[PDB]
Amino acid sequence: SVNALYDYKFEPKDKVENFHGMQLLYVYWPDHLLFCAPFALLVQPGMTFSALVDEILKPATAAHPDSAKADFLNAEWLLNDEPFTPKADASLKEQGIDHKSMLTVTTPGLKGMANAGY
Amino acid sequence: SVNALYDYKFEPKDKVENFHGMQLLYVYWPDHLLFCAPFALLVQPGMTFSALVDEILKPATAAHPDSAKADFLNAEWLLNDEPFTPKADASLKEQGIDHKSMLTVTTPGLKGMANAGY
Amino acid sequence: KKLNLKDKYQYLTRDMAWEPTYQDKKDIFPEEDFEGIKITDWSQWEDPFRLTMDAYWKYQAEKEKKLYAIFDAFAQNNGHQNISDARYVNALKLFISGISPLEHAAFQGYSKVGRQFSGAGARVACQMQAIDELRHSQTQQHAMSHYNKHFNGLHDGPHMHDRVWYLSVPKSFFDDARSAGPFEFLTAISFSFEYVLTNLLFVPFMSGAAYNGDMATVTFGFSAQSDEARHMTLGLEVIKFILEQHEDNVPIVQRWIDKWFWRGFRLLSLVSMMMDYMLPNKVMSWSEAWEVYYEQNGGALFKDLERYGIRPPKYQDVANDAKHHLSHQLWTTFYQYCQATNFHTWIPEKEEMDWMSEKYPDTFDKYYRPRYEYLAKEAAAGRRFYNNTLPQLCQVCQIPTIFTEKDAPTMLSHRQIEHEGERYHFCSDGCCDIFKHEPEKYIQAWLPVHQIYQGNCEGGDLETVVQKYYHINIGEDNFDYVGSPDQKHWLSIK
Amino acid sequence: KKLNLKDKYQYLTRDMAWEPTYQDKKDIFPEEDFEGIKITDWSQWEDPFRLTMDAYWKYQAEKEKKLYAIFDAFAQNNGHQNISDARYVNALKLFISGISPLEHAAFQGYSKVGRQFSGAGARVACQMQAIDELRHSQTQQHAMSHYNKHFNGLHDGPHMHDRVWYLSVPKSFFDDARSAGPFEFLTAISFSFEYVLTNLLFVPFMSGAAYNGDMATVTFGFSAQSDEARHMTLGLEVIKFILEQHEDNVPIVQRWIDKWFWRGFRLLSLVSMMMDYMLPNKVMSWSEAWEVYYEQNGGALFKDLERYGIRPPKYQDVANDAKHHLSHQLWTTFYQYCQATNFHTWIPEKEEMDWMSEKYPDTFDKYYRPRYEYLAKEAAAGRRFYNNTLPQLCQVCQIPTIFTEKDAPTMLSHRQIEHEGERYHFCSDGCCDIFKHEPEKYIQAWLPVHQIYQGNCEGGDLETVVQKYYHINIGEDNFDYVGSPDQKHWLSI
Amino acid sequence: QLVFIVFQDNDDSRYLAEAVMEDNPDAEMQHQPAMIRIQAEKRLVINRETMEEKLGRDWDVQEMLINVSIAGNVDEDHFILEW
Amino acid sequence: PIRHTYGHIARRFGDKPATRYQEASYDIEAKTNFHYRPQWDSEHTLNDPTRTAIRMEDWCAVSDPRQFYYGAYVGNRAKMQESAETSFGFCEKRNLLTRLSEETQKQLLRLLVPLRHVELGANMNNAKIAGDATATTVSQMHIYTGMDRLGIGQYLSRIALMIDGSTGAALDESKAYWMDDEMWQPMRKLVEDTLVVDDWFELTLVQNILIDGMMYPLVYDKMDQWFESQGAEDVSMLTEFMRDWYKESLRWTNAMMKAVAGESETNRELLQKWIDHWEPQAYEALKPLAEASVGIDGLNEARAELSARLKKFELQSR
Amino acid sequence: EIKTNSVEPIRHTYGHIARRFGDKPATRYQEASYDIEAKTNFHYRPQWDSEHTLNDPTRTAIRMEDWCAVSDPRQFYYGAYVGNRAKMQESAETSFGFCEKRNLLTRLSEETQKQLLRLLVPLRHVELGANMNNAKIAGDATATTVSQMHIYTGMDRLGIGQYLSRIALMIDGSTGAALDESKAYWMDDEMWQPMRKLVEDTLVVDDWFELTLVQNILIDGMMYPLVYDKMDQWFESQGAEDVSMLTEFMRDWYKESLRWTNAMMKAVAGESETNRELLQKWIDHWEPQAYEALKPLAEASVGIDGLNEARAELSARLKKFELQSRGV
Ligand SMILES: [Fe+3]
Ligand SMILES: [Fe+3]
Ligand SMILES: [Fe+3]
Ligand SMILES: [Fe+3]
Ligand SMILES: [Zn+2]
Ligand SMILES: [Zn+2]
């Protein structure tokens, strides 16, 4: 706990409330270290899963050779480390993909380049 | 003359007596500035003019493309700036070529390279 | 009997102080208790160095006259043309915006702590440190000035230090230290940064300059060594003092050593990258440097502290193993994001890669060489890779979460936690543990990537933030070294 | 009544000296009469500058501290690796062999003169000059110290100065000045060399070192700039004072100006070749340097002296015409004799020659470019030209007789005379006239070529004189730059 | 004709040069590399007063010397080069 | 040359070559986007200009006319320290203070040496200000003056060590006057009270203007001239440093007051409220010292000098 | 430790340094002082001297196989010398500034001031003689190790004459009238004539070693202890104690000068018995003249015993070189 000369208590800087109507979402695609770190996305809570896969996710991943041959959406997903099965037509909100959640999508059979993880 | 605080009179450093029975001779070959300055030659008082030409001058001038067809013996000579007619078989000294004389040898129609007297 | 050396110096310092009668001592010194550290007896303080003011002035002046003679000769002879290659200047860009501001923050930090310690000896020591830090801060501005005139990326470092994404790494490191109380400030900076980790910052830059033809920087490095010798003695004496003053100080000091070793280690990731990739002529690999300055030297230091009940920092084994990955991991993170940086990246030359192969025999060719093979193809093809999506940042060190698990260089060591209904993410267990002990501190962090998305960086687009907020001049300060203005200015110089 | 700046300083210098009672003035100062110069009133001497010892020590110390920090930093950092190329160091070989030893000789000359003058003011001014030249001598040893370690030919400069053929040029110059009496020393060195010609020596070297990445040599130059200011001022204050002191001084002084201009100008030949050829990056052509620093400034200065009855130096016109030739003539001389030098020569690059064509539009292509074309063809055929026969030397300046008649660039200006049964040869009328006025002095000269032939240079052939007498390491310090160890060392970076 | 003073193309000499270009508006300043040359017809001057208001300190003449060749007749009190 | 100076300097002074002082002193500090609130302060942020109630459009309107960046300050101080070292070596060798009567020695230990304690207070006060002022032009002037106060105390400390042959016995003694002697208790009380002022600009006014502005002239001028009448004139050589230093400090403390007062009527009335509460406490701290020595008209003639100087800022005293 | 790139040199020092000291790095002092001068093949004889060449070791009758046996234990090359002196000059300025501002000399009684203009200030004319004598030695001695020490010390004489001159200026408030009063004592007072005649006699000595002996050992060896040690203490009894801060420079200078002059003497006398014989003959001649020159000054101030002690102090120094003179 923080030691301080007063009651050391503050609002979080990255409260959902500061994002003007949007959320943050992180996506981690294992074995594709071309992208050095999971993406940080600024996203509609109302947007659907496939709107997310098609409007935001496939674009962000385009630069990698596997992105074409990849079918995210029917790849294996994790939400906040817990096994997840997305509802394509459901909003992100209405399926518990909230502010600063991280999705991990693993595309098995697509494990990047040169047996690195790239 | 010298201002000095005593009678300022010294023997010349380059008197002939300092040359171990040899003598200094300079030779200037005009229009052959390949050799930057007249040669300073150490010669025998008793060698012939002809030995001078064949043993000393010819090898000294050998680097110039004109040297092979020069006929130095029969060229135009000056001794200490006066016209001079070599005796091929007389000794250098006998004919007035004394210590630190300069011979100038002009070779008619051999005037060096590139119209530059080089 | 005539005073001793120790005692004459105490008389010229501590003796000037006195027990207050008209003000309570805890009002004159209000910061010494809230951190949980107890000091039993201040009159057991041993001075780390014993320079009276007249001596300090004398020595420093002689040093400064020589230093500025050199800075002036270098500028006059255009010594910046004598460096190995203009790529090298990128190390100086990183330095002046990432490191040099830390010297100024330290100046500020030590001035404060040289008011707030009740031991008068601790004060003189802190204050001598503070003015030294200010010397460093100001001599670096002068050292870098003639470079700033000839190259890009150096023209607004303090401005960028407050704003630019990657510069929040060093900036937060020091805001964490300075917002903490005085004993943690000392443990974090004097001990952790200036004793334990000091050579991992100093030697790569200063010897990186000697190997690369930079006389100005190497000259500042030599001229500062006698200051750093004092600061290291301050760091080691002070934590032995704290450790000795009370049994209960030990667990607090341990916890602090774990924290700042890890935070300093993450800060030092910028330096690894710089030394292995940004110096055309190499000094030593980041791996050789870690091993000597940390595993061996840190090993001996930590043996000498066992006697106080101290153990070596938490996760050292992780940082040890990370030395075979760290530079490569970072260069390629910056590579793909240098549309947003005040310095260039590039693909290393083939002899550079070869050297890398040799210095990293169990990792380079297996994991990192293929990266540059591919990126080289993409670039030959007119498709030089820039990643146009912002990365997840660590909530503690604020580095993009680019780090991998021990013995699994392919899996990212991401960690995540809920606190008070909010989610937060970490690059490691290291930074996760730090967060969990002080969650009320770290939820305040100004994470640059989050602030861009909040609209707080003057721009609805990264390129706009970069030019208008960051002042990084797009097409000048920006992008690959190949095709850069610096490159051309250089190929024309030579 | 409080003292003004002028009077206070004379109180701190001149007022310390006194009229002698126990010794005759003329035994204390026996060197002031024999030159013909008459001094009516030493009190008329105006202090060229007004430094007291405490201000001297203080301001010199501050310079020294900055200079040595720069020298130390240059060494630690291997700044010798930052020059344009190794050819450039040949200039510093010439500098340390030929120029540094004159700083030392000037120390000695000025020390003596800072004793011999009966005017206390003039004594301090020469004594400070003397100690400035010791500083120039020593800081130059220190500046070149790091180059001596990485490059050839700088390792035995004073030894070489006394012995090597081409170095009797500078050496006999300063021996002539110091064997002379004290007013001639002062007119020769403070006025002619240190005022009139000072820039034709310094500027090519210092700004050359500038244009060429040599921080150590520029640093000194920068540092000696305020010493030189004082050194110019004594030179002007002294001919002005001598001139005005007596009307009979005017023709003696004129003669000295003639003699020392011509001797100064022959000594500068070596500089012209250096700035035109030895600097990989060019600064200024010798032709430009002579026209600015001599034709313009010197023109101006001698005009000022018209008021005293002084005309410009005799043969000044020859020197002006020579400026189109000098460096070319000197370089080809050294080229063909560099088997016997402590420095290298080479054929200039096409781009240096285009530069020379531009700077020497009326002379280069006609007279000199064909040399390099010829020499280059021989070198390519395995026949790099070395002239194995030693040259005639001028009896006065001791430079080989390589110089051409004004307006006849193809004809050597050889002169000769007979004096007391002996023959003497000169490069020019200027040297001939200097001989005619003092033949008793110049017949003593130690002419290197003649001394080799007398067998006094510890060798029977030139290769032996060079190695054993000169300490010139054959194969290391001498020959063309191409194939030299300097070139090898350079190229392997 | 031309008097002259060359300085250290230097940090102190920047102020020294500006003191001679703002006191001799007839003076021509030219540049070679590690050097500042200032020409001018018949005379040149430095005045303690121009160097004084510019450095924010008392400034002495004898201190110019560290950085200053020269040309013409020396007159110091001021520092002026003159024909 | 792409550019002449750094962006923050060019925005301030034009795009042209800048001074060493300028490139060392303006816009070097962190200014915004701090990551964490101080655990030792609930009211302000890291690097908060609101630590003083004084308000400035731009703190860099306070600038140092001495143009001290680090190199310039140490180079100037080294030369001052060599002088003092000349003086001290000479007094030691020639026995100038050991040969004095034990009563003259006690005068020096009672009236002069306990000042080291005030120099100590002034050191801590200037340290806090260096840590609290945001602009480098201001904060660096406070670290310098701070380390100066330490130096000045070490000198007064050396007076005592010369008297006692380097045993500390005279420091022991002297310090007891400062703890126990009624003459010093108003000083000592005032010093300890300064240590507890939160407002850094209040602190600088009190310490570097009001206290120093009367104490320096009383001690190093008036009480100094009086020491001659007392048999003690040889100590004057040992306190030249203090006189040179005070004279130089007027340069920057005045320009700092000029700028801050001149800024706004509302600063001038903050300052005036602080002067009214402090300058009479300064005055009354120095009264016992002035009547035990040179007599009170020395002190009033110093109040004179201070009030006069304050009026140059449109401020007043009494 | 900062790692540097360290490069392989062809050699470590200059040929002539390496021949003398070995092929290794040399000191600044060595590279600046040894074998730097022209030694041989001089082109013309001096027009001002029929007996010797340019740079002729035979300008003194003393012989040495190597003049570099004479070396400066202070290691002064130019920059070390001016750096050392800039430090002394600053102290001197401190003290002069203080005595002027506090009126320490102008407040003296007129009789005390006259003692200063009579017994102290006129030594400026001795210092000018020594400046001259050392200039002469610098231009005659061949080795740079020897000639450079004599140029430094000659300039130091000038500097010392200047500080003494500034004592008078401080007394007369910068008018020069005390300087003129002081110089009339030097010219006219019989107290000063054996000195003034000795000084002018040294000005006419040909042999530069006989000259360094007489100036820098005999005269200085007794003058500096008499004046700056003995008459200095005595001044305290006369109410002139405050002048002492103005003559610190001279005490500091004298103590350092012992180092190089005793070093030079030791090497020269140790070289041969011939050297010793010459030196002894020069001392027998000149040392009584130095004593007699200083006697009238001692007797006007501290007393003959001050001189006898200073003479004893010179005799002890000479004993270490296997030489004798007439003290204790
Ligand atoms: Fe630092
Ligand atoms: Fe540090
Ligand atoms: Fe010189
Ligand atoms: Fe000169
Ligand atoms: Zn982290
Ligand atoms: Zn000639």
Image (tube, coloured by chain):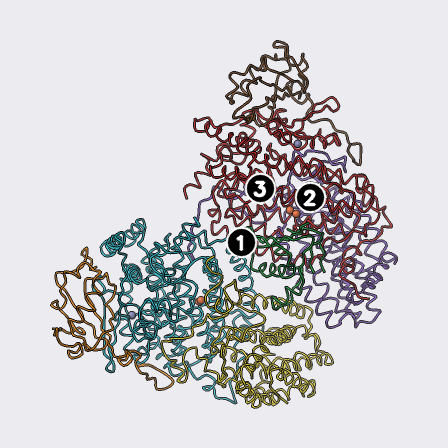
Chain colours: A orange, B brown, C cyan, D red, E green, F yellow, G purple
For numbered disc 1, what is the local secondary structure?
helix
Which corner quadrant of the figure contains ligand 2? bottom left
Labelled disc at residue D96: 3
Quadrant that contains the C terminus of chain F: bottom right
* Label 1, label 3: how far apart the Cα atoms are: 19 Å
* Label 1, label 2: how far apart the Cα atoms are: 38 Å
The residue singled out by tag 2 in the image is D299
Residue D35 in view (yes/no): yes
Tell me the chain of label 2.
D
Tell me the chain of label 1.
D
Q: Nearer the viewer, residue C443 or D109?
A: C443
The residue singled out by tag 1 in the image is D70
Could you tell me the amino acid type at mark 2?
Gly
Q: Position of residue E69 (x, y in %)?
A: 64, 51
Q: Position of residue A19 (x, y in %)?
A: 28, 78
Residue F237, compared with residue G127, is above or below; it is below
Residue F252, compared with residue G114, is above or below; it is below
